[PDB]
Figure (cartoon, rainbow over the protein chains, first blue to last red):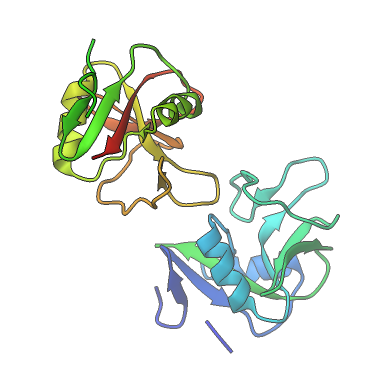
Length: 117
Length: 117
């Protein structure tokens, strides 16, 4: 929310939820899954811009991860159509009002969950 | 025309031109641009109905394309106000007397160009 269900944030057909605590990517992904959500899947620029300015100064985990031998896949499973490029050299994507890059999935960060409808 | 300048088709403040050969979306768009036109921009139902019955049995490219991360935009640049829904899952819109759907922009099809005045 801050710091669809009245407590989530609705935008462009998706319900968003922002954490108040930090977690590793997998752990956060697990926290999203509990609400029937997934680490934020970004399907557009409207989405990316909303999420970035909303993340704020602190970096937040989003649903883009790369497994060693496989290509980038969204937290939901759909393969990443690469409409945007992920900098860095790590396997998990994070974002903040400033940038959208990558860092080790072990890092504890705030995260953002989203789901359709 | 068939198969404003006397050889184009005028209707509702727009001059239309129908191709006799098939081309990919981009390539057709380039062919329209040469005449100072753009792949058909459809601003109404009168337009859509004219274009559909006129396209005929064969599918023709029209000016609606979706870039990976951006929303649907007309071939001229104006964003698509979505007054009608585009079926399919591809990024380029085509139409025929029967339907108005979407197909891969790589596909070679007849196309329709239009311009104002």
